[PDB]
Image 1 (cartoon, rainbow, N blue to C red):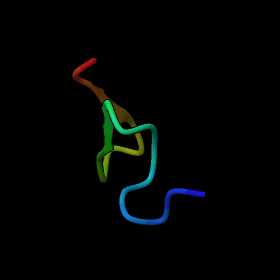
Image 2 (tube, rainbow, N blue to C red):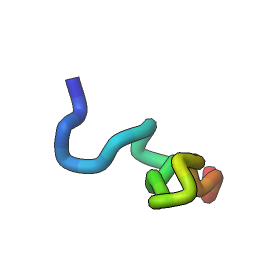
Image 3 (tube, rainbow, N blue to C red):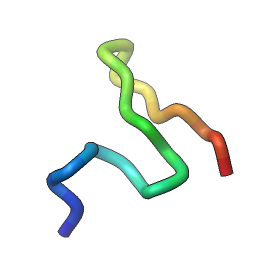
Length: 23
């Protein structure tokens, strides 16, 4: 899977434990 980020391509994971929804 994607280990070069954390979430989906349009979701940049944050240390908030959230994914940044950029679409």
